Each structure stands twice: as structure tokens, then as C-alpha cells.
Amino acid sequence: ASRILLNNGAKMPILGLGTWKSPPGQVTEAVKVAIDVGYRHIDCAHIYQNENEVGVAIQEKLREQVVKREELFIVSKLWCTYHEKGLVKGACQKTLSDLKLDYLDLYLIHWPTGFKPGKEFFPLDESGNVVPSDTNILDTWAAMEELVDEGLVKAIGISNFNHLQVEMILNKPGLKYKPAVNQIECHPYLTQEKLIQYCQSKGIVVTAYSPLGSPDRPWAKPEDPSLLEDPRIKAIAAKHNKTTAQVLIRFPMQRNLVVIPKSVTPERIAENFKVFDFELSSQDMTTLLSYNRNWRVCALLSCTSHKDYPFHEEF
Ligand SMILES: NC(=O)c1ccc[n+]([C@@H]2O[C@H](COP(=O)([O-])OP(=O)(O)OC[C@H]3O[C@@H](n4cnc5c(N)ncnc54)[C@H](OP(=O)(O)O)[C@@H]3O)[C@@H](O)[C@H]2O)c1
Ligand SMILES: NC(=O)[C@@H]1C[C@]2(NC(=O)NC2=O)c2cc(F)ccc2O1
């Protein structure tokens, strides 16, 4: 099936288009091509600095009646410098304005770590440490709940939350809305079995980011493992007459995950969507799972002393 049921009663497309690192002069065409070839979910964020341009594409396709607003599933994220109560609505409303939407289908807390508010997305001290905010995540969550009650967002969720942090929200006194989604890094080198089983056991849908191992990550090193070039994965793809990317996107689909590969390349955008026509065997799935090496693309390395840094914990 193309969509998965959320704990808010809405359906979320299991395949979406990622937009981190999509250049502002390429992303409008990338999103327009994506909608034309069947994507109905776009993953966005204010700190990707391209929401205006994503929005231009969405609006054109709504205007052209290629799609109806109800058929789209648009996701964005609250940056770390907006965890204060008083700043959450404005940050949401800036994203809405940029995307030229009157609601978000899903709004996520981008990281559990709050940072000092200001113009800087990564405010730094004299030695390069991130300057934290004393806001705690449960107060941030109440602010996210308010956004649902004001009709600005249909669902709220979290991202890069470890199991104890998901637990903290689930055990929040006075909890009004559970998180719908936890969006986390997930691929055959970071298989996330423990955290996925915890979230799914609680009715929280997991979204897999960097599913192709983010080859365009700004900090890529030559010595790093490459999913797209791993002969073992290429062999599975060749057996199925699919590309390696296509196996990497179908893998999380069969774990009941949502997945959000990024591309600005028209041919790759179309390719990446043709993953509903084949199935990986359970053996293929267990084999892909065996490649785990707890390798992360996104480790937020400037925030390792933050009290809420999520990746000291095993999971
Ligand atoms: N919540 C968070 O903290 C968080 C963190 C990281 C990512 N995300 C979200 O997850 C998305 C996906 O992650 P990501 O951007 O890190 O990386 P990714 O989707 O794993 O990899 C994107 C890279 O793969 C290339 N690519 C795409 N399709 C390909 C194909 N069929 N064959 C060969 N190469 C292909 C893209 O190239 P071209 O673009 O040049 O075609 C780009 O260089 C992001 O864009 C963002 O929306 C969220
Ligand atoms: N260092 C990290 O782990 C993250 C990853 C990350 N990518 C992403 O999609 N969400 C993120 O927060 C990101 C994106 C940026 F635009 C700038 C920094 C950045 O850092």
C-alpha cells in the first residue's frame, strides 16, 4: 500500500522527497517533477534554507490542478533555536508562509536539543560549543500540541529522539497528543532495530532519513562506507533487476517505515519512485540488516555535550 496510518487518524505516504542540500535554484523543478511522477509527500525544514522554493513548486502544482491539497503530505521541522514556548508559533508560521500553505500535515521537533535563540542556527561559544537553551523538551512538546489545537498542523512528531526521550514524551504529565512520527537515520549500515521496535510498539511511525547514506553530506570522507557502491547490495539489486538505490528505498518500506530519499536529478526522482513493483525476500531483508555497523551520517557533532544530545545512549 502507498500510505501508512498515523495515530492521529491520517494517512501518510510511505515514500517522500527529501530536500536537505537541494539547491534553491534546483529544488522548485525537483519538487514539480516529483509531483508529476507521483510523489505526494515532501520532507522540508526551515534550516534547509529552501522552503520558499519548495513552496513555489507546491503552489504551481496545486494551481495547475495536478494535485489537490488533501492529496499532499507536507512535513517540516522546528529548528533547535525555536524551542522556547514563545517562538514555536512564529517558526511554524514562517514555514507555512514560505511553503504557501495554510497547514502542515506533520510538524516535527527537529532535534531534542534546544539552542539559544537568535539569527544563528548554531550559536557558538568561544571554543565552538553550541550554546544551549534551558527549555526542556516537554514544554516544547506542549507548544507543538498548541499548534494542532490552532489548526496550523494536522500531526506533530519528533526527530532524532532516542528511546528514553520518546519515553519522556509518552510519559509527559498531561500529555495531550502522542507523537505521530519519529524521523531517524536508518539504512543497512544503521539498521536501528531497537529504536524502531520501541517506536512501533507504541504506535509511532518511523521515518527513515538518509536512506541512501547521504553521499552529498558536506563532511563525506573517502574512507567512509558507501551503500550505493557496496557490492553486496549491488548484487541484491542485480538479482531483482533494480538499481541499488531502489533496493535501498524498498528496504525500509518493507519494515513498515516511511522513507524520504533526496534527489534534484529528474531521472533519479522518477527512478526512486518505481519501488512498488517488486519485493525483497525475508532473506534479502535479513541479509541487508546484517550489514549494520552503527555508522551515522548525522551525528550533530557540535552538540555532543548538550544535555539532550541523543546519541550517547545505545538507542
Ligand atoms: N531529521 C533530520 O535530522 C534529517 C537528517 C538528514 C536528512 N533528513 C531528510 O532526509 C532526506 C534524505 O537524506 P539525505 O539528503 O541525507 O540523503 P540520501 O537521500 O540518503 O542521499 C541523497 C544523495 O543521493 C543521491 N541520489 C538520489 N537518488 C539517487 C539514485 N537513484 N542513484 C544515485 N544517487 C542518488 C542524491 O543525488 P542528487 O540529488 O544529485 O540526484 C544525493 O547526493 C534529506 O534530504 C532530508 O529531507 C532529515
Ligand atoms: N550535523 C548534523 O547532524 C545535522 C544534520 C542536518 N541535516 C538535516 O536534514 N537535518 C539536520 O539537522 C543538518 C542540516 C543543515 F541544513 C545544517 C546542519 C545539519 O546538521
Image (cartoon, rainbow, N blue to C red):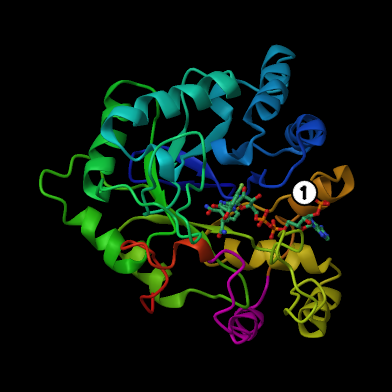
Q: Is residue 191 above or below residue 154?
A: below
Q: Is residue 147 magenta?
A: no
Is 97 rendered above or below residue 86? above
Give percent across and percent down for residue 51: 63, 30
- Range of magenta residues: 280-300
Disc 1: residue Cβ within 8 A of ligand 1's nearest atom? yes
Residue identified by numbered label 1: 263
Question: Does the magenta portion include 295?
Answer: yes
Where's the C terminus, which quadrant?
Answer: bottom left
Residue at horizontal 86%, vertical 76%?
238
Residue type at mark 1 is: Ser
**Image coords of residue 231 (percent x, y):** 82, 84
Q: In screen coordinates, is 65 left or right of 86? A: right
Q: Residue furthest top?
A: 63
The quadrant of the rendered image in which ligand 1 is seen is: bottom right
Q: Measuring 49% from the left and 60% from the top, which residue is drawn there? A: 184
Please name whichever residue, 153 or 121, is drawn nearer the observer in this view of the structure: 121
Judging depth in this view, the residue of 9 and 161 nearest the camera is: 161
- The local secondary structure at tag 1 comes to loop
Residue 190 x/y as whole percent: 56, 75
Q: Left or right: where does residue 158 sit relative to residue 15?
A: left
Res 68 → quadrant: top right
Q: Position of residue 192 (x, y in %)?
A: 48, 73
Question: Residue pushed farthest front?
Answer: 126
Dot 1 alpha-carbon crowd within 10 angstroms: few under 14, some 14 to 19, many 20 or more: many
Regarding residue 220, the answer to whether it shows in the image is yes
Q: Is residue 215 above or below residue 47?
A: below
176 lies left or right of 74: left
The foreground one among 130 and 186 is: 130
Question: Which residue appears at 72% of the width and 24% of the height?
Answer: 57
Report which quarter residue 311 is drawn in: bottom left
The one of 234 and 230 positioned closer to us in this rendering: 230
